Each structure stands twice: as structure tokens, then as C-alpha cells.
């Protein structure tokens, strides 16, 4: 409803599990490179979210001027792109967005399986993956997740507690005499960490879904920027402290909770993170469930809910076969996020306002602080070029080499991804 709910949603849906793999990224990038990449990608993700908001507002105004009703349904990103640029862009956006959301849900299932292992190690991470895959498949019966605001302003508290626990525990533990702090050793690890940060920031393809619930979506531009600033405040200290403490040992420990000594605070952090990803999975899979039902023609509950199972099976199977907690994030970030969250929105923004009449009669001009249309187009071109050459090319090469390396050394359907 109000702007506060939107801010909470943006701050809680921005980081779910990357808060635990961020120190692993730092162990590959180094302190300076990691900090610079997080800040640069935070700014770039805020910019892309602003572009997505501009496109959503433009589409909504273009439809209201024609007295379109929408029959009270969320205007999904593919619908906006269809109505604003054509059917080919509809297909492109739909495919990329749905694939990224499916892989993100897989990522949350893997994160839950990995996290629970550190409260109860009596069962291998694969058994935990089975159990939590069943628990997540239970979410099919839930129609939607937009209606809930508790799940936002509680998940933000859980993320804040986890980040501050990481920071304080790392600072108190202190680095041992045998610690080592090696910066960039090989470009593969460096670009894997950079791609993990890229995955961390950007919006996670849920911008329009966090925006439809707002009374006045025009303020989302600033709301998401402030939420990103708060998320940076959360992530920078935790990652920096965890790296400063356990430098060069995080390379083989993707999860940051595998290193810290077990205690009541660590158990609380694990429980809160599990409860946070159990809601992030739902908030990321509801969009997939809606599109699945729309394609199969079932969308208009037990009979309808049972029709959502074919969406769970790909998610449940993918988590089991590839439990690679850390490198999966880099792989998805380079292959899917680079297009889903950065390149595709920028290209859509450039094409939508390319025609002169469309640019002149737009709902709102870009801010003069960013140089108006000229500066907006320059920034969009830079974002596209950067996220392509580094996010996709170098990032894709490094992330896929690392993923194949994990497959080589641990195999498929591995019991432990890492239990040193
Ligand atoms: O691991 C991370 O930082 C989080 O990733 C994601 C990815 C897609 C999402 C889609 C919807 C809601 C939350 C989402 C979180």
C-alpha cells in the first residue's frame, strides 16, 4: 500500500542467501575489488530498477488512456513488454524472466538444504534437499504472496540480524596466525565473484511485482534506491568482516556459517535464514506458477493447485542434481541475470522511447541530474555493453568453467557439496 511497505519489500527481496556466499566472492575478488563491485552493481541495479519502473508506468498510462481495465490483475513484466514493444519482445522477456525465476527458486531450495545441515548434520545435504523440496512443493496450494506484508518487514529483520551476526562474530573471533589473504589469483575466480555480486544486485526480476502493490508507483524510483542503500549497509560489513577473519579459507567454504563456531546465535541465524528462504522461494515461484497456469489455460483450488506440480518437479530435480551452493549463483548470474535484469530492461527502455512522438509525449522526462535523454541513453548503452562483455562474456566463461570444475571434483547428485 504505502511507500513504507514497498521499501520493506524491496529491502527484503533483494538478498535472501547471497548474504552467505558474499564472503566467498570476496575471497576470490579481494577486499578492494569486492567493495568496488558491490557499490558499482548496487548503483547499476538501482538504475535498472528505475528503468523498469519507467517502462511499467509508461505501459500503464498507455493502457489507461485507452480505458483498459486489467480486470484487477498484476501487470507482469512480459505483459508490459508485449504491450510496449511487440510479441517478439514478449517471448524474449517471458523466457528469460521465467527461466531466471525457476533457477532462483532452485537456488533458494539449495540454500535451505545447505543451511539446515549446520543445525543438524545427522543427515546429508541431499536428504535435507528432499525434505525441503517437499516443504516447498507444499507451497503450490498457496495462491499468491503479494497479499502479505509481514513476510516483508519480518524478512528484512531476519536479513539484518544475519548480517550483523556475521559481522560481530567475525570481528570477535579474530583472524588466526595461519590466515592468508590472497587477492586475485586467477581470472576465473575473480570473475566468478564479480558475477556473484552481479547476481546479488539488480532487482531479481521482481520489480513490477513489488511495484503493482503501490498506490503511487512513481516513488518506487527513490524507494528502491534507499532500499539498495540499506542492503549495501547490510552486506558490505558482513562480507568484509567475514573475509578479514577467514581469508583464503572461504574459497572452499561457500556458506559463511560453515566456518563460524557453532553457538546459540549461529543456530538463530540459521533458523532465520531458513525461514527467509522458505518465503523467498514462494515469492519467486508464485510468478512462475501464474505463467504456467496461463500457458496451460488453467489460470482463471485443489484441482488447480495439483496442476502446479509440473513446475515444482524441474525445481526439485535441479536442486538435487546441482547442490553447488556458491557457484550456482555465479552461473545463473552470468547466464540469466545479465540478460533478465540488466540488458533486457535497458534495451527495452532504449527502444520504447526511440521514436520521436513516443519520447515527446512520455509520462515523465528523465531527471536532469542524469543529463536528460542523452545521459539516460548513454547510461543504458554503457550498462548493456558492460553487462555483456563482463557480465556475460568474461563472467559467463569464468562461472561456467568454475561450475564444470565443481562437477568434475564433486560429481552429480553429490551427498556433500562441501563437508570438510
Ligand atoms: O540469492 C539472492 O540474493 C536472492 O535471489 C533472488 C532471486 C529471485 C527472486 C525472485 C523473487 C523474490 C526474491 C528473489 C531472490
Image (cartoon, rainbow, N blue to C red):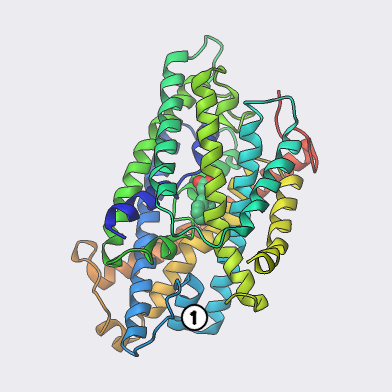
**In the rendered view, does 36 fall on the left or right side of 359?**
right
Which quadrant of the figure contains the C terminus?
top right
Corner quadrant of residue 409: top right
Q: Residue 206's x, y, as percent?
A: 46, 60
Q: Residue at x 64, y 49 (%)?
A: 136
Residue 405 seen from this side? no
Residue labelled with disc 1: 82
Q: Residue 161's x, y, as percent?
A: 42, 31
Seen in the picture, residue 266 relative to 133 is either above or below; the reply is: above
Seen in the picture, residue 278 relative to 145 is either above or below; the reply is: above
Corner quadrant of residue 65: bottom left
Q: Which of 221 and 133 is in front in this view?
A: 133
Residue 254 seen from this side? yes
Q: Which residue is drawn at 38% across and 47% down?
A: 11
Q: Which residue is situated farthest in the front direction here?
A: 302
Q: Residue at x 42, y 68 (%)?
A: 346
Q: Residue 128's x, y, as percent?
A: 71, 37
Q: Which residue is drawn at 48% across and 55% down?
A: 204
Q: Residue 104's x, y, as percent?
A: 59, 53
Seen in the picture, residue 408 relative to 294 is either above or below; the reply is: above
Amino acid at each position: 500500500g504505502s511507500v513504507y511497505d514497498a521499501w520493506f519489500s524491496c529491502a527484503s527481496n533483494q538478498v535472501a542467501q547471497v548474504l552467505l556466499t558474499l564472503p566467498y566472492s570476496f575471497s576470490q575478488l579481494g577486499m578492494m575489488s569486492g567493495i568496488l563491485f558491490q557499490l558499482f552493481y548496487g548503483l547499476m541495479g538501482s538504475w535498472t530498477a528505475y528503468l523498469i519502473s519507467v517502462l511499467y508506468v509508461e505501459y500503464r498510462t498507455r493502457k489507461e488512456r485507452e480505458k483498459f481495465d486489467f480486470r484487477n490483475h498484476v501487470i507482469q513484466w512480459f505483459e508490459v513488454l508485449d504491450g510496449l514493444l511487440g510479441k517478439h519482445w514478449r517471448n524474449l522477456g517471458l523466457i528469460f524472466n521465467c527461466t531466471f525465476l525457476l533457477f532462483g527458486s532452485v537456488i533458494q531450495l539449495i540454500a535451505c538444504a545447505s543451511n539446515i545441515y549446520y543445525i543438524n548434520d545427522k543427515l546429508d545435504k541431499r536428504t535435507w534437499t528432499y525434505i525441503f523440496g517437499a516443504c516447498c512443493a507444499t507451497t503450490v496450494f498457496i495462491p499468491s504472496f503479494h497479499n502479505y506484508r509481514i513476510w516483508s518487514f519480518l524478512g528484512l529483520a531476519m536479513t539484518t540480524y544475519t548480517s550483523w551476526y556475521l559481522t560481530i562474530a567475525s570481528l570477535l573471533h579474530g583472524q588466526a596466525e595461519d590466515v592468508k589473504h590472497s587477492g586475485p589469483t586467477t581470472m576465473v575466480l575473480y570473475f566468478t565473484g564479480a558475477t556473484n555480486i552481479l547476481y546479488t544486485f539488480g532487482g531479481h526480476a521482481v520489480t513490477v511485482e513489488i511495484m503493482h502493490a503501490m498506490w503511487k508507483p512513481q516513488k518506487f524510483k527513490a524507494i528502491y534506491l534507499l532500499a539498495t542503500i540499506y542492503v549495501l549497509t547490510l552486506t558490505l560489513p558482513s562480507a568484509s568482516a567475514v573475509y578479514w577473519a577467514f581469508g583464503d579459507k572461504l574459497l572452499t567454504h561457500s556458506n559463511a556459517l560453515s566456518l563460524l563456531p557453532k553457538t546459540g546465535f549461529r543456530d538463530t541465524a540459521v533458523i532465520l535464514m531458513l525461514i527467509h528462504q522458505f518465503i523467498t522461494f514462494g515469492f519467486a515461484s508464485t510468478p512462475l506458477y501464474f505463467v504456467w497456469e496461463k500457458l496451460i489455460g488453467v489460470h482463471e483450488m485443489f484441482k488447480r493447485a495439483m496442476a502446479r506440480l509440473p513446475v515444482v518437479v524441474p525445481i526439485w530435480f535441479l536442486a538435487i542434481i546441482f547442490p553447488f551452493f556458491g557457484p550456482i549463483n555465479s552461473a545463473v548470474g552470468s547466464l540469466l541475470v545479465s540478460f533478465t535484469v540488466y540488458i533486457i530492461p535497458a534495451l527495452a527502455h532504449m527502444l520504447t522511447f526511440a521514436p520521436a512522438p513516443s519520447r515527446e509525449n512520455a509520462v515523465e522526462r528523465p531527471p536532469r541530474v542524469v543529463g536528460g535523454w542523452m545521459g539516460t541513453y548513454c547510461i543504458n548503452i554503457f550498462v548493456v555493453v558492460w553487462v555483456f562483455v563482463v557480465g556475460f562474456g568474461f563472467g559467463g566463461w569464468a562461472s561456467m568453467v568454475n561450475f564444470v570444475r565443481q562437477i568434475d571434483t564433486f560429481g552429480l547428485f553429490t551427498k556433500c557439496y562441501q563437508c570438510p
